[PDB]
């Protein structure tokens, strides 16, 4: 709304805070009266009578509670009054509640009931609590209250197994305390700062219940924190439509009905108000208001008043006296007792002869404290926060035992200990407020609590509370304590800061969001009901009835303030708010907005300590601090001595603040009372203010100031300067020895090279030489070393190895130690790279490898530095100079192949009508790259390399070579490899069409199953495979003729040799080269690639001559690419994504307003959030549905097919999204809508970037990192993924260009410019992945000695690159002897590992041979470490379920980065499965399948994306099982092998051994099983032997469903068996036992296995196993594939003459129930 | 005459605080570095000082107490008459406004073994038309004790604090200057025998086209001006490859941080 006004917020503030009194009059209970005395007035208010148990409100017995909740009232008989009235609302409903009652009336027990209701929601059927399904937040105003609540709640709920805890001020390591806690107890501010920070799968989604205790803090200057929490919670709730219950606990004060509106309490269901007659003990009140103004006379008046009241209670009642300074406790108790002595009244307290005297006298002798000494024997005591714990417990136990007579204390007692007293006196209501910089009145919460301690719940018949204050405050305290001080909103002051926090979170993105947010504030409710109180005329209100305009004005004002201070960029015309990094820091560090403006203005890279202290001292948190005349001499004394000079005078506050901080760090004692409290305030703030400064200068890269400010953070925390002995940080080390060490100036570092003796001698104290030596080596210390790996001449990869070099001890290191790794330039001025490093206790002895990139230039600079500095320990750092004097840089890369300007090639150039029919409907001409390479591809047999950007049509280039192959050889075999299975599937579709359909050849896609893949290879002309599927096949090329007789080998996306799965691709390409050299009929190779800077090395490795090497660079893409890389300078991920949301929309409207757009986002969740946010933005553009290009009615039939409603809404507005969690049908529907132009925008998760069948005009890549849950860290997108994403901006048949915007963190921008605008350098990583391949080559006898292994390596890409970029591979030169030494070293390492693993043997240290274990690993394509683990764990009596556990723990299984919240679901799966599993550990990627296998097996559940997960796991399971079989079979054991075979069956059919076979049949269930048991049939054959009518009747099934049953029954194995023992008589002891077994199928079936729950299509496998179960002995075994009839031999030795009866087993790997036994 | 009417109390206002405040502003001068070119004829060697280490040298210095670094370098591959200064070495030292006190031991480190010593650089508070007699004496005594310091190749660069700037000037000794300086025992400002012909100006250029580096002591820092008692002409030291701390850094004045701790 247009005519906004700018308001003065300061003129709307209630300056008195909680002392503001909105009521004009105070009415007093009947029988009150006012007495006059010299210089003061007394007001007396009598005790109230309890309401006399009207309404027959009986006390509810714990019996009639719900049984789950009775345990929470163990040891109670009934409820008390208030809980009985609150029971139904609290325990039997989820209504939000507000309870008003006098403090001490029971409100906390009602909160207990709400907690019990919540806990009840999470009962298992075993009675336990799923403690991981929920969090409860209990917000309490005071820290001492937090602690007491953690204790009492924890004891009440321990029977439930529930953990209650508080949160530490340290959260960057201790956020596991949130994960461990079900009931979090904290202050408003703590929960505010925690929820201000938006993270990744944080636990705020578990919050179901929030209790706001003492919610009348709303009236305090702290109250706005509660408003922020409630507005944030309610808006989050509506955002996510998950309910969260809110409970408010309040004193009884006016406006409670407005508090209930604020909490969304229904006044008829959840509002309960109990007046002060419900106090547990009636209260006679005395108020004493002094009229004297002269301080001197006023203080003695007060002391005479307290003495007279004391005297009224001496010897009849204990008195608790509350004062407001720890020192005042002693001074006041002393004034009173001195007056008693001088007046001779001390005998009234301490009677002579009474037993209480006798009890006191003991510690009246002992006396631990000094003031306690002077006062304890007289009957007086003090209590406060400078005293010990056991002194305080002394005071508490003594007072509670009715021994102390006069206890002087402070508010902390009132909040933190449950110690009441008959008489309470509040001695003055003035308290010194450092933050206000002056004396003010005590807060109301404090007053209420202290007077709530008057009267003890069972001893006293009444309490007597006496409040002494100044006369002008009488009406305030009278109002507060008699239900009449109204609760108001203090929010107007804090509005800019609160608004920024919501902008930073993304909850408020424009002024209308902000008006909506303000509508949930307590302020808004109060503005509506009392407008004039808040600066609004009654006629202003009538002209603006929902205060829309006034809220707009307040929001506008605050936003302008935030914009002036650079926290926010505020667009006045649109109302939009743009987050900034400085705004984020202000919110996340809880800093006021003026302060971060000061910091932004004054922080410079050149600042020294002097100016850094000055900057801190100008923070606005300190703006009320003044320099008082009386403080000026002492301050001057400190100034002239401070170690950091102060430039300004002691007239200015900032100099006092500076000096106070420095005095704190030096641990100086000050004398002035004001100076000490001011120091406390300043230094309590300093930690988080200085960490904010640290984060600012670190992220700007300011090396020296980053160092100075991290040091200052640590000096504030440790309370010492750098110069002090770092050993002071071990609190246990006695100060004297440390001072002795310091006196000697020698370096602490010297201590490392000494021992017990020399250490004792150097400081000349031998008695300590040992423990010093201990502490020296507990001091955190890290050794560093680097491997420099040049990428180009201007980019260097660094692998940093961190080695811990100290002894860990949980007593000083906790469970982790954090460090900053800072990579700094030549001058130590710029931080080129940095990152956080966490050393966990469990890895404390392990080396850690970190890898990062830095820029370099020529001429090379002298050196960089790597500093690793502790985040917490002072003088704990290691710096490694990284010299470049010996860095070997790779050769500058060559120019690209020139793109010749040729006549576009018509399709007719194929000179073949059948061939031409594949393209002539698609286009008339081939593109420039196809035209350039065509002659070489199509008219020569030369090996070809084509390097070009994704989207350049390289696939057609390979088709040219295939068509040449088809003209040379009628049964030519082309094998085609691509690295990604999704690509393989797409190529399969397209080429099945081109070459099978219109050309009548055979196209096949390898599946991964050996024998069927061999059949595909034999009959296919085009064979499509991913790399591992061709690796396992081509390993056996010496015995597979179809592998050698390959005409054409095409490898696509060959630049991925440099990425994560590159080694296997390198290996198979190298093998194809080696074969082609061994068979003298060369295999033509064609390699396709993204543009490569070192293309010539790939070409040369693959045998491509330089005229056949086409090495094009990115600017040749046939559809020109307009690439824009846009940097975002925000280091926190969720906030950075927020800052990207609007630019996404603006990029669409600028670069592609009408043409299709793909937005890639980092996560599944973000796809939906960004689709919604785009829609929101185009609605606020008054351009809703601009992305919808078909009509809604044409879209509805589509929309019905989906299960996601949100997806339906967004799709209705022209925006789709794609993420892993969508059913394949849904994904296809969205892709169809996108490609048919019906919807214009699709948002896709990054993980789909390889398997999308859509393309766009514009691709937006929104951020370039994703969260890895395995390692709990953000990972950069591989450059390969980014190139593949950019490639989707390519529509040759439709666009004149493609456009792409990459939005990335600013510190990534340079990297992308280097590796997207230029061709890509790739390296090998085969040297990190050698063992399985060496092992395979030893099995097939390609490697028979160490020389063979070196020769083998010479065929690799690794070998070529070693001469081109030696330092990358850790060579230090390229000489042939360097090469030979390096290769020999690598060979010796690999073969030694394989030998230790028992995969191979090594004889005469030269010759290698395969061991049967190596042969198994190679045959089944299993990692050698996996098979070693198998060889270990397996034995002759491992249980089946143990097998499941073994197999789950195998290198093969590392696939889960999503779910930790299903760890509890698996915990309960452990009970559902009969697996008596051992070691109930949890949460591993391998520990999923430990029982997620069984989740598949029982058919237990189909669930979520885990479905996809299961499909990969099952993929590897059979092989792993078969390996175990093989292991057992070789050992000689008969039983566990058969167990493994039946487990193969189990996995295939998804059943178990004890379960019923009938579970195999389609459309079956348990009821059918018990019916077939009732008839007496238990076999598949049984079902086959039935009459068709009776068959159809027994099953109660549909016709088509029994047709499914019939197809299964007609492929079920029914094999006739026969055996013959060759020469059964003529069998001599020692000779051969040739047993023969002939098997004949009954109908030679030709389908694969019927196994719907198993993913891959399987062929049927069999084992003919002759053994004797007499002793777990297997004697002969053969695997077989049976087609129709098979004849199988088995050989065996006959040791000695004797009993000769053997058992022949026929075991399937696929079906359960066909396992035979003959003799 | 007021014994009692007017009493006043002295309050320490110590010297080094003001100088620390001043030293914090030194970075401003690194934008205004001038080299005097009043020499002529271009005959001797030409010295090229990389700006990065010179700026750092200025930033770690003091307005009133001189500091010194040792110069190490080489000639470009094909110009033997050009000396490129590649490294400055900071060693334990203290200074006055008129001279610096260095150990007798020269830098020894393997990492320097491929360079030649080129002399030394020092700051001084004010420009001067002449090379001071203290500099001549210091250079001549170094050469007398270290034959690796060639009189035709080792220079003194002076870094003078001019208005808002620094002015650099480079000199070398002559034979007669060596002979007078090596026997000169008069540390004052006007010792007998001192002559303008005991030195001559040499050509120096600043460069941004390469970068120098620093070496500093391995276990101490270089600045002993706050603990001269711990400094000794005969002290020995090893070196490390790292950048020097500024003059008033806490590690240079630890007694200020332990003594304040006594109130
Ligand atoms: C303060 O808001 N943050 S929260 O308490 O964790 C919350 C999460 C979800 C719904 C409601 C509240």
Image: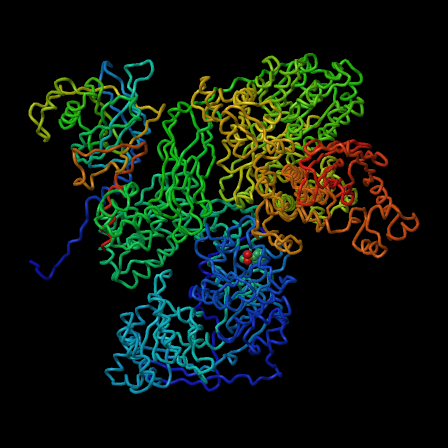
B95 up-or-down from A644: above or below: above
Above or below residue A1336? Residue A1469 is: below
Q: Position of residue A830 (x, y in %)?
A: 39, 35
Residue A410 image point, x, y percent: 37, 70
State the image quarter where residue A1634 is shown: top right
Q: Nearer the viewer, residue A1636 or A1350?
A: A1636
Q: Quadrant of the C terminus of chain A?
A: top right
- Residue A229, horizontal then vertical, whole percent: 53, 59
Q: Horizontal placement of A936 versus A1193: left or right?
A: left
Q: Nearer the viewer, residue A1381 or A810?
A: A1381
Of residue A1660 and residue A1402, the one placed in the foreground of this image is A1402
Ligand 1 quarter of the rendering: bottom right
Q: Quadrant of residue A1546?
A: top right
How many numbered marks have been drawn onto this rendered protein structure? 0
The answer to whether residue A1154 of the structure is visible from this angle is: no
A1699 versus A809 height, above or below:
above
Q: How is the image coloured?
A: rainbow
Q: Is residue A1028 visible?
A: yes
Residue at horizontal 28 percent and vertical 48 percent from the top: A725
Is A979 on the left-hand or right-hand side of A849? right
**Residue A1621: percent from the left, percent from the top?**
77, 34
* Front residue (pair A685, A26): A685
Q: Is residue A1427 left or right of residue A172?
A: right
């Amino acid at each position: 709304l247009a005519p906004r006004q700018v308001l003065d917020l300061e003129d709307l503030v209630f300056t008195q805070g909680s002392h503001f009194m909105a009521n004009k009059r105070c009415q007093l209970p009947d029988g009150s009266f006012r007495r006059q005395r010299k210089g003061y007035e007394e007001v007396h208010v009598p005790a109230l009578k309890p309401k006399p148990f009207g309404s027959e409100e009986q006390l509810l017995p714990v019996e009639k509670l719900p049984k789950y909740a009775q345990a929470g009232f163990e040891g109670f008989k009934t409820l008390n009054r208030i809980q009985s009235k609150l029971y139904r609302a609290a325990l039997e409903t989820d209504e939000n509640l507000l309870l008003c009652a006098p403090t001490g009336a029971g409100k906390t027990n009602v909160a207990l009931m709400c907690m019990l209701r919540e806990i009840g929601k999470h009962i298992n059927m075993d009675g336990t609590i799923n403690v991981d399904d929920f969090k409860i937040i209990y917000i309490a105003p005071m820290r001492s209250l937090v602690q007491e609540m953690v204790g009492s709640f924890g004891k009440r709920l321990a029977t439930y197994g529930i953990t209650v805890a508080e949160l530490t001020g340290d959260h960057q390591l201790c956020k596991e305390e949130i994960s461990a806690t079900q009931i979090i107890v904290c202050t408003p501010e703590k929960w505010d700062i925690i929820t201000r920070k938006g993270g990744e799968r944080t636990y705020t989604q578990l919050v179901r219940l929030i209790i706001l205790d003492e919610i009348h803090l709303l009236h305090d200057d702290r109250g706005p924190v509660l408003e922020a929490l409630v507005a944030r919670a309610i808006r989050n709730i509506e955002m996510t439509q998950e309910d969260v219950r809110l409970i408010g606990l309040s004193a009884t004060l006016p406006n409670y009905e407005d508090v209930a509106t604020f909490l969304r309490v229904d006044p008829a269901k959840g509002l309960f108000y109990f007046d002060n007659s419900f106090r547990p003990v009636p209260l006679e009140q005395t108020y004493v208001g002094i009229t004297e103004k002269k301080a001197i006379k006023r203080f003695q008046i007060m002391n005479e008043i307290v003495y007279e009241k004391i005297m009224e209670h001496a010897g009849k009642n204990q008195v608790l006296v509350f004062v407001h300074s720890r020192k005042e406790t002693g001074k006041t108790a002393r004034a009173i007792r001195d007056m008693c002595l001088e007046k001779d009244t001390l005998g009234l307290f301490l009677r002579e002869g009474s037993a209480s005297t006798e009890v006191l006298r003991t510690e009246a002798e002992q006396c631990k404290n000094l003031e306690l000494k002077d006062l304890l024997p007289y009957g007086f005591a003090i209590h406060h926060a400078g005293m010990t714990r056991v002194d305080r417990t002394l005071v508490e136990d003594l007072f509670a035992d009715k021994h102390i007579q006069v206890l002087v204390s402070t508010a902390t007692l009132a909040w933190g200990v449950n110690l009441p007293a008959h008489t309470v006196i509040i001695k003055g209501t003035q308290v010194y407020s450092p933050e206000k910089g002056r004396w003010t009145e005590l807060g109301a919460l404090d007053i209420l609590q202290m007077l709530g301690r008057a009267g003890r719940p069972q001893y006293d018949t009444k309490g007597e509370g006496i409040l002494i204050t100044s006369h002008g405050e009488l009406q305030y305290y009278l109002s507060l304590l008699n239900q009449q001080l109204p609760i108001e909103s203090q929010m107007v002051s804090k509005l800019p800061d609160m608004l920024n926090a919501e902008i930073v979170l993304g909850n408020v993105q424009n002024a209308k969001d902000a008006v909506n947010w303000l509508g949930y504030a307590y302020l808004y409710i109060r503005m509506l009901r009392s407008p004039t109180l808040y600066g609004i005329s009654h006629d202003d209100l009538k002209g603006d009835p929902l205060l829309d305009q006034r809220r707009l004005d307040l929001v506008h004002t605050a936003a302008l303030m935030l914009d002036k201070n650079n926290l926010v960029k505020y667009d006045k015309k649109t109302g939009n708010f743009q987050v900034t990094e400085l705004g984020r820091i202000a919110s996340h560090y809880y800093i006021t907005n003026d302060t971060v403006q000061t910091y932004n203005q004054l922080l410079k890279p050149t600042l020294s300590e002097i100016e850094l202290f000055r900057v801190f001292s100008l923070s606005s948190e300190f703006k009320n601090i003044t320099v008082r005349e009386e403080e000026k001499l002492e301050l001057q004394k400190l100034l002239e001595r401070v170690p950091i000079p102060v430039k300004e005078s002691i007239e200015e506050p900032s100099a006092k603040i500076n000096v106070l901080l420095q005095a704190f760090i030096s641990q100086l004692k000050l004398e002035g009372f004001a100076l000490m409290a001011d120091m406390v305030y300043v230094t309590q703030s300093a930690g988080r203010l200085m960490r904010a400064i640290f984060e600012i200068v670190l992220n700007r890269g300011w090396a020296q100031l980053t160092d100075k400010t991290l040091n200052l953070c640590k000096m504030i925390d440790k309370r010492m300067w750098q110069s002090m002995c770092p050993l002071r940080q071990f609190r246990k080390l006695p100060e004297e020895v440390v001072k002795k060490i310091e006196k000697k100036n020698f370096p602490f570092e010297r201590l490392y090279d000494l021992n017990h003796n020399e250490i004792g001698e150097l400081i000349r104290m031998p008695k300590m030489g040992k423990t010093i030596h201990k502490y020296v080596h507990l001091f955190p210390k890290l050794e560093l070393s680097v491997h420099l790996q040049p990428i180009t001449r201007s980019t260097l990869k660094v692998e940093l190895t961190i080695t811990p070099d100290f002894q860990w001890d949980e007593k000083v290191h906790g469970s982790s130690e954090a460090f900053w790794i800072l990579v700094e330039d030549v001058d130590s001025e710029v931080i080129l790279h940095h990152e956080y490093f966490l050393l966990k206790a469990k890895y404390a002895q392990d080396e850690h490898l970190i890898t990062f990139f830095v820029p370099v230039f020529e001429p090379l600079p002298p050196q960089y530095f790597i500093r690793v500095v502790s985040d917490r320990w002072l003088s704990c750092e290691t710096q490694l100079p990284v010299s470049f004097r010996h860095l070997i840089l790779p050769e500058k890369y060559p120019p690209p192949t020139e793109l010749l300007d040729l006549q576009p090639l018509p399709v007719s150039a194929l000179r073949n009508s059948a061939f031409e029919s594949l393209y002539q409907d698609k286009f008339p001409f081939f593109n420039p790259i196809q035209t350039q390479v065509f002659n070489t591809v199509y008219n020569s047999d030369d090996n070809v390399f084509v390097g070009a950007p994704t989207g350049s049509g390289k696939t057609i280039c390979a088709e040219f070579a295939i068509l040449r192959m088809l003209l040379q050889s009628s049964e030519g075999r082309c094998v085609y490899i691509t690295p990604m299975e999704a690509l393989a599937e797409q190529v399969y579709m397209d080429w099945y069409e081109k070459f099978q359909d219109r050309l009548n050849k055979k196209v096949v896609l390898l599946t991964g199953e050996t024998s069927t893949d061999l059949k595909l290879l034999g009959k296919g002309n085009i064979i499509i495979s991913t790399p591992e599927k061709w690796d396992i096949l081509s390993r056996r090329w010496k015995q597979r003729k179809n592998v050698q007789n390959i005409n054409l080998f095409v490898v696509d996306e060959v630049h991925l040799i440099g990425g994560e799965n590159g080694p296997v691709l390198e290996v198979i390409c190298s093998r194809m080269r080696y074969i082609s050299s061994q068979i003298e009929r060369p295999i033509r190779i064609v390699a396709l690639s993204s543009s490569l800077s070192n293309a010539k090395d790939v070409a040369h490795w693959l045998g491509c001559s330089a005229t056949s090497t086409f090495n094009f660079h990115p600017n040749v893409r046939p559809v020109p690419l307009e690439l824009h890389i846009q940097g975002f300078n925000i280091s926190h991920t969720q906030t950075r994504l927020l800052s990207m949301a609007k630019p996404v929309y603006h990029a669409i409207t600028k670069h592609s307003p009408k043409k299709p757009v793909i937005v890639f986002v980092p996560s599944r969740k973000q796809t939906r959030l960004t689709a919604i946010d785009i829609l929101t933005t185009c609605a606020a553009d008054i351009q809703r549905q601009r992305f919808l290009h078909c009509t809604e009615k044409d879209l509805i039939p589509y929309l019905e097919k989906l299960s996601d409603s949100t997806l339906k809404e967004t799709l209705l507005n022209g925006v789709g999204y794609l993420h892993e969690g969508l059913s394949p049908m849904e994904r296809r529907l969205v892709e169809q809508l996108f490609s048919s132009g019906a919807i214009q925008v699709v948002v896709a998760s990054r993980s789909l970037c390889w398997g999308m069948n859509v393309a766009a005009h514009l691709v937006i890549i929104m951020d370039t990192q994703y969260y890895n849950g395995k390692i709990h860290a953000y990972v950069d997108y591989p450059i390969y993924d980014v190139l593949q994403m950019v490639g989707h901006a390519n529509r040759p048949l439709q666009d004149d260009e493609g456009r792409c915007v990459i939005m990335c963190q600013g510190s990534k921008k340079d990297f992308f410019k280097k590796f997207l605008y230029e061709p890509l350098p790739v390296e090998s990583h085969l040297d990190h992945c050698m063992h399985d391949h060496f092992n395979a080559e030893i099995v097939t006898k390609t490697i028979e000695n160490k020389q063979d292994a070196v020769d083998y390596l010479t065929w690799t890409f690794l070998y070529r690159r070693m001469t081109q970029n030696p330092n990358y591979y850790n060579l230090q030169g390229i000489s042939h002897r360097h090469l030979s030494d390096h290769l020999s070293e690598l060979v010796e390492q690999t073969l030694s590992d394989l030998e230790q693993s028992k995969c191979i043997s090594i004889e005469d240290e030269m010759d290698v041979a395969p061991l049967n274990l190596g042969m198994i690993a190679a045959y089944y394509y299993i990692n050698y470490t996996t098979i070693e683990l198998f060889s270990m764990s397996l034995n002759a009596k491992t249980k089946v379920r143990g097998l499941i556990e073994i197999i789950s723990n195998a290198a093969e299984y590392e696939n889960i980065p999503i779910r930790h919240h299903e760890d509890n679901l698996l915990r309960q799966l452990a009970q559902k499965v009969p697996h008596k599993l051992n070691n109930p550990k949890f949460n591993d990627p391998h520990v999923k399948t430990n029982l997620l296998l069984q989740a598949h097996l029982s058919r237990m559940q189909l669930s979520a994306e885990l479905q996809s997960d299961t499909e990969e796991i099952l993929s590897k399971a059979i092989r792993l099982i078969q390996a175990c079989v093989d292991v057992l079979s070789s050992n000689g054991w008969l039983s566990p092998a058969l167990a493994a075979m039946e487990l193969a069956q189990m996995v295939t059919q998804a059943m178990w051994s004890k379960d019923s076979y009938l579970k195999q049949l389609p459309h079956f269930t348990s009821e059918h099983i018990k019916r077939c048991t009732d008839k007496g049939v238990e076999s598949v054959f049984d079902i086959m032997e039935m009459e068709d009518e009776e068959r159809n009747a027994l099953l109660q099934l549909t016709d088509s469903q029994i047709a499914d049953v019939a197809r299964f029954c007609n492929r079920y194995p029914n094999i006739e068996l026969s055996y013959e023992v060759v020469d059964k008589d003529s069998i001599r002891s020692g000779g051969p036992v040739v047993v023969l077994v002939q098997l004949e199928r009954e109908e030679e079936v030709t389908g694969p296995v019927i196994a719907p729950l198993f993913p891959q299509k399987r062929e049927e496998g069999w084992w003919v196993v002759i053994g004797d179960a007499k002793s777990n002995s297997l004697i002969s075994i053969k695997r077989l594939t049976l087609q129709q009839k098979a004849k199988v031999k088995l050989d065996f030795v006959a040791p000695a003459t004797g009993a000769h009866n053997y058992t022949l087993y026929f075991m399937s790997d696929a079906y359960m129930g066909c396992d035979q036994e003959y003799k | 005459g007021p014994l009692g009417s007017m009493t006043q109390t002295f309050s320490s206002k110590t010297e080094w605080r003001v100088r620390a405040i001043s030293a914090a502003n030194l970075h401003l001068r690194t934008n205004h570095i001038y080299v005097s070119s009043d020499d002529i004829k271009e005959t001797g060697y030409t010295y090229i000082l990389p700006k990065n280490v010179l700026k750092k040298f200025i930033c770690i210095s003091d307005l009133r107490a001189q500091i010194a670094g040792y110069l190490y370098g080489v000639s470009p591959p094909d110009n033997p008459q050009v000396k490129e200064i590649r490294c400055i070495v900071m060693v334990p030292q203290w200074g006055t406004h008129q001279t610096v006190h260095l150990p007798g031991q020269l830098p020894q480190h393997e990492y320097l073994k491929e360079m030649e010593p080129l002399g030394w650089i020092h700051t001084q508070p004010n420009e001067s038309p002449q090379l001071s007699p203290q500099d001549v004496t210091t250079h001549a005594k170094i050469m007398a004790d270290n034959p690796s310091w060639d009189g035709e190749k080792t220079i003194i660069i002076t870094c003078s604090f001019t208005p808002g700037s620094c002015t650099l000037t480079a000199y070398k000794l002559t034979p007669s200057g060596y002979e007078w300086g090596r026997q000169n025992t008069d540390k004052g400002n006007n010792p007998k025998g001192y002559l303008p012909s005991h030195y001559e100006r040499v050509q120096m250029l600043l460069s941004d086209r390469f970068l120098g580096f620093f070496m500093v002591p391995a276990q101490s820092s270089w600045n002993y001006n706050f603990m001269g008692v711990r400094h000794d002409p005969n002290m020995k030291y090893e070196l490390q490859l790292a950048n020097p701390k500024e003059f008033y850094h806490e590690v240079h004045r630890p007694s200020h941080f332990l003594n304040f701790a006594l109130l």
